[PDB]
Each structure stands twice: as structure tokens, then as C-alpha cells.
């Protein structure tokens, strides 16, 4: 006291808030590609005919 | 780019619609035959009259 109030520091209270991954469980496949665009070819095959 | 964009292909997608074997579960016997026809004899014998 007098010059300055003495202190005890008790431990720091770190709240690290995060956004845990949920939707990325349905995007498991990863592609790293340098080409300009990605492309899909989707095919329908009606093999149900008699 | 410029002339024509480079593309990275992802795997092809195939809506391959089969028609699964359901009724054929009740047709388990197979007969391969070269005779012109197949024939059955069916006999009804009512031994239940007084």
C-alpha cells in the first residue's frame, strides 16, 4: 500500500471460442488442382428396361 | 485460360438404375432343355366322399 496496491495474480481465464466442424463431414474428399476449373460428367443409365 | 480453360476432371457419376431380382426368389428351379415343350401331369383324388 501507499505507493501502490500489492496484488496476487490468480490464473488467467482464457475463453477460446471456436466453430467446430460439422458440415465438412459430408465433404471428405479433397482435391488440390491447379487447372482453371473443375468439371463433372454425370451419366444416367436406364438399365431397367425389359 | 485465355484460349480455352483448363479443366480438372472429378470422377464420373453414374445413375445406374438396375431392376433387382425380387419375384425370381420364388422361381429357384432352373431347367435348360432342348425339347420343344415342358409338360406336367396334375392329379386330383378326392378320397373324402361318404
Image: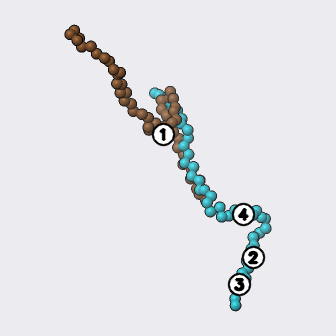
Chain colours: A brown, B cyan
The residue at the point 65 percent across, 64 percent down is: B26
Secondary structure found at label 4: loop
Query: For mark 4, what is the residue?
Result: B29
Please tell me whether residue A14 is drawn above or below residue B36 in the rendered image.
above
CA separation in Å, label 4 and label 1: 45 Å
Secondary structure found at label 1: helix
**How busy is the neighbourhood of tag 4: few (under 14 within 10 Å), some, or many (20 plus)?**
few
Do the residues indicated by labels 2 and 4 lie within the same chain of the protein?
yes
Count of all numbered marks drawn on residues in the image = 4
Q: Position of residue A17 (x, y in %)?
A: 37, 29
Secondary structure found at label 2: loop
Q: Residue furthest bottom?
A: B50
Please tell me whether residue B46 is drawn above or below residue A47 in the rendered image.
below
Q: Are marks 3 and 2 in contact (CB under 8 Å)?
A: no
Secondary structure found at label 3: loop
The residue at the point 52 percent across, 35 percent down is: A29
CA separation in Å, label 2 and label 1: 61 Å
Do the residues indicated by labels 1 and 3 lie within the same chain of the protein?
no
Q: Are marks 1 and 3 in contact (CB under 8 Å)?
A: no
The residue at the point 44 percent across, 37 percent down is: A22
Q: Position of residue B50 (x, y in %)?
A: 70, 90
Q: Are marks 4 and 1 in contact (CB under 8 Å)?
A: no
Host chain of mark 4: B
**Which mark is on residue B46?**
3
Mark earlier in primary sequence (4, 3) = 4
Q: Are marks 4 and 3 in contact (CB under 8 Å)?
A: no
Query: For mark 1, what is the residue?
Result: A26
CA separation in Å, label 4 and label 3: 29 Å
Q: Is residue B28 visible?
A: yes
Query: For mark 2, what is the residue?
Result: B41
Host chain of mark 2: B
Amino acid at each position: 500500500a501507499g505507493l501502490y496496491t500489492t496484488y496476487q495474480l490468480l490464473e488467467v481465464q482464457r475463453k477460446l471460442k471456436t466453430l467446430p466442424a460439422f458440415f465438412l463431414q459430408w465433404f471428405p474428399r479433397q482435391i488440390n488442382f491447379q487447372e482453371d476449373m473443375i468439371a463433372f460428367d454425370k451419366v444416367i443409365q436406364d438399365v431397367t428396361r425389359v
